[PDB]
Image (cartoon, coloured by chain):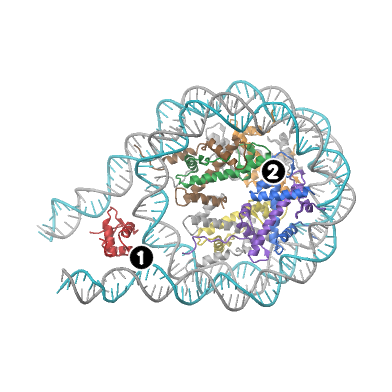
Chain colours: A yellow, B green, C red, E brown, G purple, H orange, I blue, K cyan
Amino acid sequence: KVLRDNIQGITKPAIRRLARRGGVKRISGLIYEETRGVLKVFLENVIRDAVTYTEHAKRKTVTAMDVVYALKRQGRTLYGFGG
Amino acid sequence: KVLRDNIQGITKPAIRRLARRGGVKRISGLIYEETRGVLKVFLENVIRDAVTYTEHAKRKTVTAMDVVYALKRQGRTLYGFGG
Amino acid sequence: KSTDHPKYSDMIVAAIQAEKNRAGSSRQSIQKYIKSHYKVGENADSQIKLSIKRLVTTGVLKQTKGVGASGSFRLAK
Amino acid sequence: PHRYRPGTVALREIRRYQKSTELLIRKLPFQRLVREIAQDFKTDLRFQSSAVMALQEACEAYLVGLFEDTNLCAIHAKRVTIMPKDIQLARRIRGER
Amino acid sequence: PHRYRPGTVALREIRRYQKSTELLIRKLPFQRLVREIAQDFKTDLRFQSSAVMALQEACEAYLVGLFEDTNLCAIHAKRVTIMPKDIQLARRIRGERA
Amino acid sequence: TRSSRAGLQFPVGRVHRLLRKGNYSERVGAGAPVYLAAVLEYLTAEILELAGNAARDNKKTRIIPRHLQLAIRNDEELNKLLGRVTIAQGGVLPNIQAVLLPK
Amino acid sequence: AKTRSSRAGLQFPVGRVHRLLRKGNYSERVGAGAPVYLAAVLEYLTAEILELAGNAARDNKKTRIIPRHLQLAIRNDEELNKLLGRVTIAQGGVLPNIQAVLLPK
Amino acid sequence: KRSRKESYSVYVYKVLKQVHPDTGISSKAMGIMNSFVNDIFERIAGEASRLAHYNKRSTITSREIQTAVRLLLPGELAKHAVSEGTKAVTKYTSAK
Amino acid sequence: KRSRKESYSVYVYKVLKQVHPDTGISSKAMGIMNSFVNDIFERIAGEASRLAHYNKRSTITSREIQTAVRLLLPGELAKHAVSEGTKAVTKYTSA
DNA sequence: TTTCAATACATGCACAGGATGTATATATCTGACACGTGCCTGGAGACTAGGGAGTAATCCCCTTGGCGGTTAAAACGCGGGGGACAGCGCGTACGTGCGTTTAAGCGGTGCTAGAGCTGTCTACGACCAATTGAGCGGCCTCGGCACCGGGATTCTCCAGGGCGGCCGCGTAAGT
DNA sequence: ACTTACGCGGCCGCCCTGGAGAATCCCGGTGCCGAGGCCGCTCAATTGGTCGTAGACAGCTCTAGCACCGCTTAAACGCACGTACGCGCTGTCCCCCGCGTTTTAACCGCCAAGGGGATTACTCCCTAGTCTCCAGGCACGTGTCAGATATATACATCCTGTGCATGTATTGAAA
C-alpha cells in the first residue's frame, strides 16, 4: 500500500523557523513546496541505499550502521553515533 | 635561486580567449591579476604534492605517475594518459 | 544677480530657463544647477521637489514625462 | 496599543535560535514520512529511532546549509527576501542539479 | 569605412573556440612558471613534458569551469559583464575559499 | 580457456589473478570474475556504440576523444557516472546564452 | 617493562594497533615501528583537541565538555575546519553570525 | 634492453569490430579506455572489499559483487549489468 | 551474559587528566572521539596501503607512514607529528 | 477684422532593399600512423591432496510496534498598514574594433653526459609455535553535579513634544 | 490709492528626552549521570628456529638538457565613441505583526512476540604443488585516411532609403 497526503507534514512554521536559523528575514511562496520536494528527493537518495544495505544484511530491520554507511558514502560523514 | 618576473606570462589575450571559451562577453580589470594569482595557488597545491611523491620515489625527475596520483587525490581524476 | 535669496519657485523657473533641450530640463539637472548657483542648504534643497509640485499644480510648469516619472519640466508661454 | 516595525522580533528570534541545539522538526511526522518513503522500495520493513534521528539531523544540516547559501545569493542579488531562483542557482553551482 | 557594433565578432569567436580542442596557453611560459614554483620547495629538480601538459590541461579545465560559474553568477546578477565579486562568490559557494 | 566456456571476450584468468594479488581478500571465488568481465564488456560495448554513433554523425571514420567527450556530456547516465572526471582534449559543449543574443 | 607502550613512553596501545594493521588486510608484511609513529601522532592530535575543548569549556563556565564545545573549537580554528570540511557534527549547531546589511540604521 | 608491458587493446578492438565493422581507434582513445578500465577495476574491487569487511566475512563471492554493482550504478544500468552477469554465469555453470 | 565490545575511553581519560586534571566528558563526546579515531585509522591505513601499492613494495615500514602523514596533513601540523613520531621511536630504539 | 476646421506641413517610426567581408564544401596531393604478420616465451592450464571456513537446525529473551487517558502549547484563520518590489528618464565614462610597429614564440640541427634502468650477492629481520599470566572488560552502587523554577534588574528599541526656513494671511508708508 | 518696510501666521524636518517589555543576573531543592570499587578470563608477553625479501655493487646507454639562425605571427602602443552600468525618484500591493480559536505532540502505563542473537556438526569448496603448451609478449615494413590548400560560393549583418501620424502657421471664409 502506497501512502499519500504525508508530504504536507513540513508546515509553514517549520520552514519559517529553519529560515530564521539559517539567517533569512523574509520568505516568498513557492519555496515551501520546492524545498519540501528537494527534501523528499534527498530522503530517497538515502533510504534507497539504506534498503540496499538491509538486503545485503539478510535482515528486516534497518539498523543505524546502514544509515551511517549510506551517509558516509555520499561524502557527508555524521558523527555523534560512534558506530 | 628564486625566479621572478614570470607570473606575467599569462597575458591579456590568453585570459580573453579563456573567457571567450567559457562564454564571457566582456571582462573588467582586476580579474586578470586575481585569476592569475589563483592559478599560481592551484599550481602550488599540485606541485608540492608532486615533489613529495618524488621524495617518496628516491628520484630526481618528476614522472607523470606522480602528477596523476596528485591530481587523483584532489578529487579531479584526469584520463588520457593511461597510467 | 545673486544678492538676497529669492523664492524657490523663482529659482526653479530661472534654472529651467537657463537650460535648453528638446525633451525638457531634467529635475536632477535643475537641482544641481540650483545647488551650484545658490547658497541654499540641504533642507532648503529638499524643498525643490515640493516647489516643483506646486508650480505644476498651479500651471506655470508643463510636464512632459513618461507616465509620471519626474522626467522633465518646461515653461509654458 | 503598541505597534512594532517589521524586523524587530525577527533579529531577536534569529539570535535566539543561534544558541540552542534542540530539534525543530517533530519526530512523529518525520517517522511517518520515512515509513511512507520506505514502502516505495520494499514492503514489510522495520526501523529504529537512531536511524530516524540520524536522518533528521542530516536533513536539518543540509537545509540549514542550503538556506545559508540562498541568503548569501539573495544578499549578492541586491535584495533581502530570498527567492526560489536563488535556491536553483545555489544547487546549480553546487553541482547537485 | 565600415563600423561594427559591439558583440558582432564576439559571438563568432565564441562559436569558433567551442569547436577546436587545441591549447591556448603557450608551453614555454607555463614551463618556466612551473620551474619557478618548483624552486620554492626543493632546488635542483627535473621535469618532463607530460607533467607540464597535464598541469596545463588541468589548469585550463579549472579556469574554464570557474569562468562558466562566474558568467552564470553575472547573468543571475542582472548584469552582463563579469566582476571579481562573482568569482569570489563562486569560490565561496564551491567551498574552496573560507 | 574459461573465456570461451563463459562466452566472453575479456580474460578471466587475468582478472582472477589481479583480484587475488591486489591484496583485497585471502579467499576469492571463481565466479565473481565472470560477472565482472560481463559487466565490463557490456559497459565497453555501450560506450563504443555511442562513440561510433558520434563518429558517424561527424563524418569521421575513426573515433577521437572529442566524440567520447560529446557522448559523455550529452548522455545523462554517463555524465552522472563521470561527474568528477575531466577528459583531456575534449572541450565543452556548444552553448550560447539567451540574454546575449541581439534583438 | 613488559608492554611496548611503556617502553616507547606513550598511552595508546601498540599491540592492539599492530594487530589491527596486520588483520585489516592492508599488507602481508608489517613493520614493528610504524605503530609507534601512528600512536604518537594520534596522542598528539587527541591532546590538542582536548586542550581546545577544555579551553572552550572553561570559557563557557562548564565543568564538563559537550559536543557544542567541540563544534565551536572546530569551526573557530582554521586547521581543524580545513581538516574536517566535509564532516557534519551532530548536536553542534552553527556559529553566531549576523549579517551586516540586516542591521537597522 | 626491453621490458614487457600489459595493455587492454585486443579486447577493445574485438568489441569494436563486433559492433562497428568499419571503425578504428587512435592511441589517446586507447589510453582513455585503459584508464577507465583500471578505474572501474579499482572502484569495484574497493567496494567488494569494503562490503566483505562490513559483513564480517572473508570470501568475496557473487552476491557481494552483485550488491556492489547495484550500489555503485544508479538503477537501470545496474539491472542490465546484473542480467549480463547472470546469463553468462548460467552458461558457465552448464559448462565446466 | 553480554557480548564483549571494544572502546577507546581509558586512553582519552588519561590524556584529559594529564592535560586538564579537573575536566570531564560525556557519552556523545566519547562517541565522537571514537568515530574520529576510527576515521583517522582508516584514512592513514588506506594512504599507507596505496603508497605501498604504488611503490611496488610489499612491506609497510616507517618512511611510508611518515610520507603519508606529511601528505595527508597540510604542513606545520605534519612536521610536529613527524617529531612526535621520531622522538618516541628513538626512545623505543634505545629500549 | 474674428470664429472654426482643413491642410500643409517637419519628427520619430515601421518595412523592403543593397553592399561587402566572412563561414563553407570541393578536386588535389603528399606523408606519416593504422594494421596485418612473425617468432620466442613465461604466464596460463590440467590432475591430485587438506582441512577449516561456511551452510544449516535449535533455543533464549531484547526490544519495536499498538494502543488508551490526558493537558496544553503550538497550529490555524482573518485585519490592516508601512515600506519593499518593480518600472523608468538619464549621465558620462569604459570597454570593443581597428588602425600600426617591434619582439620573442616557434622550428631545424648538433652535441653531451647525469642518472634512470637492469642484473647480481646474501644476510638482517620477519613469520609461526608452545606456555604464562596480568591488563582489560561487564554488573552494583550512590553521590555531587546540574535541570527546572520564582523573583528582581539593567539593557535596547519604538513613538511623542518643541523649534526653525519662510510664505502668503493682509497693513502702513513710499513713488 | 497701491507696493514693499515686514507684522505675524501656520506647516514640514531633526533631536532628545520618555515609557514599557524582553533579556539578564542571583538562590532553592531535587535527580539521575559521571566516577570509583570489584573480579573474571582471553589476548598480549617470552623466546627458539628457518626463510625469503630487502640492502647494496656494478655496466648500459637514453632521455634530460645547453647553444644557434632565421620566420612569420602573436603580442603590444594607441585613436575613437556608443552602449551598458549606475544614481535618482514614484506607486502599489504583499508579507510583517498582533489576536480568537482548535487540534494533535510527548510523556506514561501496559500487553505481545518477532526476528536479533549465542551454540554446534559436518561437509563441500578453496589452497598448494608438479607438469606442460598455446595465447599473447613485441620487432617490422608498408600503404591508405586525411593534413594542407586555391578557387568559387551562398549567407549574415550594418548602413541607408522610404511610408506615415500629430502639433502648429497662414490664407481663406466668416462675424
Q: Which chain carries label 2?
A: I
Q: Horizontally, is A63 left or right of E23 in the view? A: right
Q: Can you say whether G99 is above or below I61 in the image? A: below
Tell me the tag on residue I50: 2
Residue K95 in the image, given as x and y percentages of width and height: 48, 63
How many numbered dots are placed on residues in this image?
Answer: 2
Q: On the rendered structure, is A34 left or right of H83?
A: left
Specify the quadrant of the image occupied by residue B39: top right
User: Depth check: K65 or C21 in front?
Assistant: K65
Say what secondary structure mark 2 lies in: helix
Rendering coords of residue C27 (x, y %) = 32, 58
Residue beneath disc 1: C43
**Image-quadrant location for residue C69:** bottom left
Crowd class of label 2 (few under 14; some 14 to 19; many from 20; radius 10 Å): some
At horizontal 56% and vertical 45% (from top left) the residue drawn is: B41
User: Which quadrant holds the N terminus of chain A?
Assistant: bottom right
